[PDB]
Length: 124
Image 1 (spheres, helix red, strand yellow):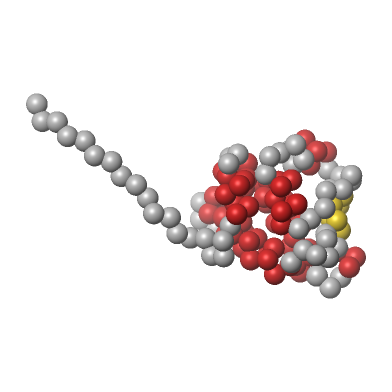
Image 2 (cartoon, rainbow, N blue to C red):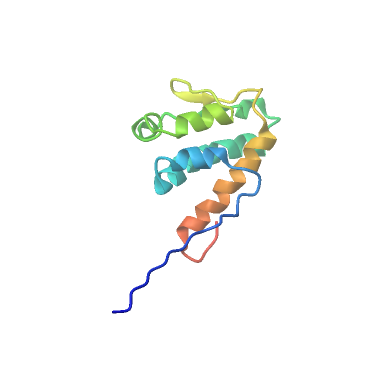
């Protein structure tokens, strides 16, 4: 009989300004990274929105949910530490050495990815 088989492949292109945290996090899971990163994005939003306000240089996170799925999670801890954060006891502190311009640049990737994962035909 007639025999014959083939294969395929992909290229890859979408990352605006790099995205190391995305790749490192993806090592765990797509859905997990999206949610695990979502929280980090929201926290950075405050600093990015009001970087001059030293009062917003800190991020409260006493929610037991964080200690349940955010601390022991592989990717989130390294993400904040690598990006430019400080793991506290009850809340996280924003290092003055951290680059807000960089956080936003990379944050844009997750911001758009959030809606891309929804695929529910809608916006924020």
